[PDB]
Length: 56
Length: 429
Ligand SMILES: Cc1cc2nc3c(=O)[nH]c(=O)nc-3n(C[C@H](O)[C@H](O)[C@H](O)COP(=O)(O)O)c2cc1C
Image (cartoon, rainbow over all chains, first blue to last red; front, side):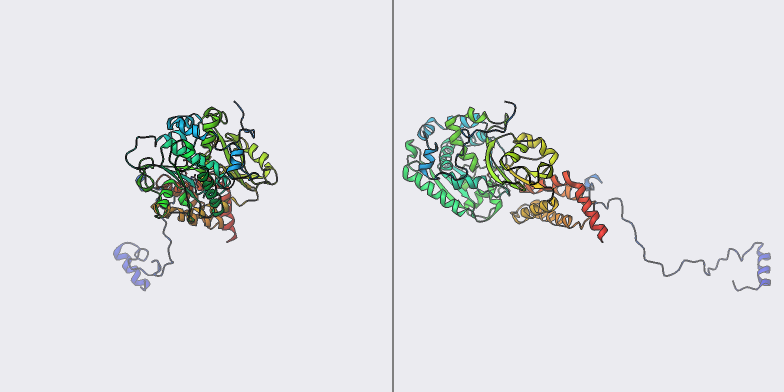
């Protein structure tokens, strides 16, 4: 956060905890908004043999 | 008897297989044909049927059904409709050329067989359905039938027995499916060569809606010799329930391809190495052999080493006797390519009526082409096996079974080659 050391110390004392560690606002730890393309797997019935529907 | 596979020339039914004698009436009579035919007909249908049953004769068409009971199916009181005998001379099974020799070089034997069979089944006439490509053979058969008519052997008062009988030759038009009995009946009736659905069986409703019996050329031509020389003599050759003398066509990679009338239950190795000079390059160069044409699954060299050429022995060997067309492939043969070509043949010779046949045969053809190219995956072999099993038993004709069986045999006996070729294709790309 863009908070000065005096303000950070006052905030931590008033709260009683280290707020600068577990900040609620998200800055950079979020995942990227442009993720690589995926490749999802097929299910257990995507086989060319021994897969008659009467058995499942 | 214990060991079979050595027939003496005195016992061979077809004594003019190679056309080294006259194929006309004089030659046939000199070779024993038409002897005491009047007495055979005057014996009665029951006597002829009993002789056929005692001979242990089984169908030479490929089904191997007991001939005696099949013919006796027609032995019923007349219901006001005529009865016919139909001779299956289509001979479309790849590797099968035995009926061609019978028609071309021993035609009077076939005519006498038609007469005897019609007397046994009380058939008014006989429609011989010869292959359309067999035009010279059809001409020879027509000449023989004309000679029989002139001599009084057939026609009104056939051989003086008081039995009226006609023999008709109907040429084919180029359909392998017309080899099927019901499809042949449909072709004779003038429709498309699409097999019927049983029941009704031909013995009740057949050609023109009349009781009928379809039979192979060899099965009909061996009947006069069975009646004359005796059922016991015919049964004396071959194993029990596999009795008789069988015509064999030995094609493929053999030194001397030919056709010989050996005894049933002859060892396959003895048949190949004696009458054909063995496999090209020796018996140690034999990859696989198709024993019964194309509809029968292949067998590897290990099976071919000790196997008898009869119905039961080949049935135990996960194959069939069929038309006894021994296709021989050496170890230089692309077995996958050969099986793919057979499946392509079945694709091009499919009536296209039943859904499993029409769709699945083409599907398997495409899959086999991709296997030949190697452009597939190892998981597709079991898929192809399942497709073949879905085709087999679920069709109208047995052409579905006849197209599934080669694939099943290939998958059963050479799966490592398929997987290896798939690996080769994968590595190259
Ligand atoms: C696809 C197919 C092709 C056939 N081709 C022939 C053939 O060329 N010659 C033949 O005698 N039987 C052939 N058959 C068997 C016939 O349907 C019939 O069973 C046979 O002609 C009668 O044999 P049999 O009377 O000697 O027992 C074929 C069957 C099928 C399913």
